[PDB]
Image (cartoon, rainbow, N blue to C red; front, side, top):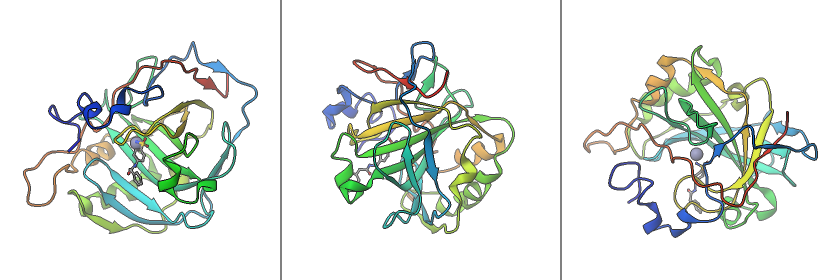
Length: 257
Ligand SMILES: NS(=O)(=O)c1ccc(CNC(=O)Cc2ccccc2)cc1
Ligand SMILES: [Zn+2]
């Protein structure tokens, strides 16, 4: 099946998922000088105070921290969005080296990792319906650079030992995703897709300008995870990122100048 290796990675995906070469694929390079400031953009509303995390899962491609999305407890609204988008999960993409790992790039610059907080539009009722819609998803993307540690990330890195291999899950309640956000909510936004198969073109991407910093020890712990299942040959979960895709007929908008 698809993955991130030489024989099943991003260059192969189009054979099973032809939309890989579609009109609104993600990630993209954000050319800061060509992004258009849009004063018609409302401020972002991140409402995570009632967030209820449930579980953390190694799915063989990344690890997901899952939330209760059966009511409006943690939602994203405003910005470019119309309506209410419910937080379902967050996950990261990261590199084998500090100089690569993010999916979006900024003036071709790669960050060490990228956080994706995935939300779905409540007017579609469930996540499965949402991904079939052009405005079904809103993913909040946050770059990570290596430097000082991120205290709000530590609880996540300390549980990774318990989900080392594909298919492992562990209880992960009472985690506050507000601890992963930078100070500023200045953002760029563009219409794109899921960055893994099925690569559906259902995402309003909202990528924050300000990266968060994580420590070298923190990202090293990401790199100790496994793509494989228990009892299978060890393949380190690193470089689980999709490179930048053609922008084509899209303008990236900025919330700030
Ligand atoms: N990296 S990203 O933030 O763009 C990203 C990628 C994949 C997904 C998950 N998509 C699927 O698992 C498939 C699926 C389809 C229909 C019902 C359920 C699942 C979420 C977010
Ligand atoms: Zn992602």
